[PDB]
Length: 121
Image 1 (cartoon, rainbow, N blue to C red):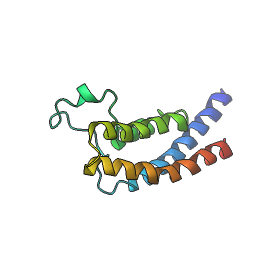
Image 2: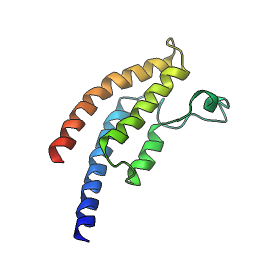
Image 3: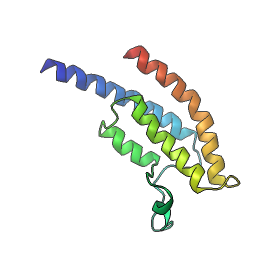
Image 4: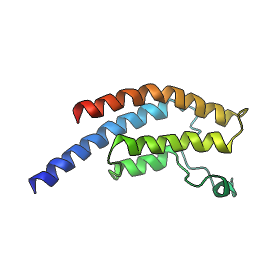
């Protein structure tokens, strides 16, 4: 149908907007602390602590599979990265501090993407 196509065009454009958002968020992690999944070889007990692991490479796989239907779903995954880190790591660590900074700095980017998604529909 012509409707399924128009829908596929919007999803593709949302995917394009979310790709730019992802790149902006990831620039706010220059140390690449959140770039890849926490290693289960190096933190064998991680899943006893954190039930829904997340990271930027895993979000990127989902993104490129057009697996995000809206900004809310994307934000949920970004919040997991931050929230997982702030539970697993203590306050006085480079990792916890890096999540606080990513959270504060990403908020500006997410604030405008919400307006752009509402705006362009």
